[PDB]
Image (tube, one colour):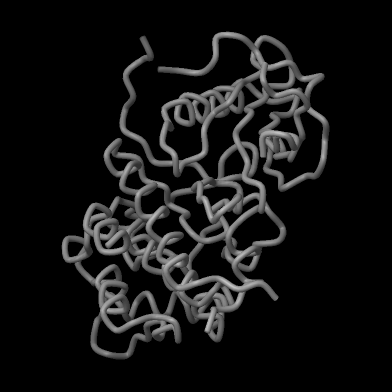
Length: 305
């Protein structure tokens, strides 16, 4: 019923009817000549996402600035251009330390470009999956909770705006110096994460709540379910895929069992690094009834303290 993929490949947010801006993007277009291509993160139907460096960004500090660049095709239809510009207005509202920010745009010419901040160490799945827990590089358990706490605060902020992410996961959490986290939305565009999506729509079924799969009902409570799975990833140091032993069909089968709720379902097991109390809170995010799932305000309080 619902497609989540945006025009340039990434996933889009579910947003209320937004008042016209009267906050917003920069009034001046970003000089394209200042974008040095580095890599192609992913692609969509009418565009692509690039990683680019920027020299002398005054117009981490000493090194060059990494940025993601959404690029619409020059031959994009008027509907595609309107969709891209809907994404712009949404990303222009995002102003939080743990959320990516719209840094510039290139509208007055072709192709349409969206410049957003990008973190130094790429996404958290690739970075964390190489670490091991302290008794390759190592990470402490307090630093893990520090990562999870930032993700909670990011969603808490999105919750205050009535935004719904609909594709939260470690692959959409960007990491930089000192385990600074910024939530983003590029993973859906990446070949590297195809296994995380089921073709139909193309959906991240392993992170979706049962009502997203069986009714297409995405809400803040369904982002809490995804945050539950994401927290599980972090405490597993991103070593395995959620329900990785199951096929994509068995994952939909399992969603029906969450709905039937007769004990035939299976939940993710407690990660070795996870205390009992944190696992219990993790399980509350997977409650059958949306209302029984914790709010991000309460998740942020537990993880920060």
